[PDB]
Image 1: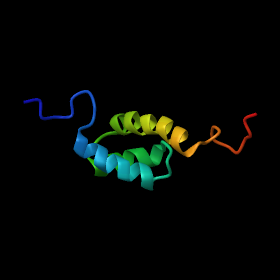
Image 2 (image 1 turned 90 degrees about the vertical axis):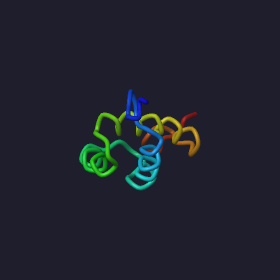
Image 3 (image 1 turned 60 degrees about the vertical axis):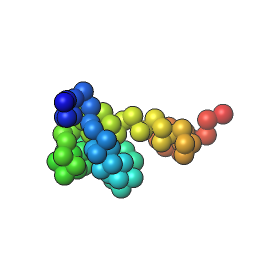
Image 4 (image 1 turned 135 degrees about the vertical axis):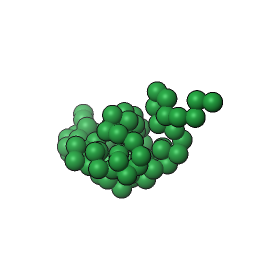
Length: 73
């Protein structure tokens, strides 16, 4: 029962998404989202919602001062 992508993507999708995240450019992209979403078996909405959540974790783990090279003192 409820064997569908209700509310958010399923585990199987996270597998394709994680690969995509590590292969695209580590950033939510417009052209990229639509194209990769279709191949992942999702839509932009779902891909955006997922990619953005990893964005926060990415910044924590890799330690990035925002986007550009700026020394946070």
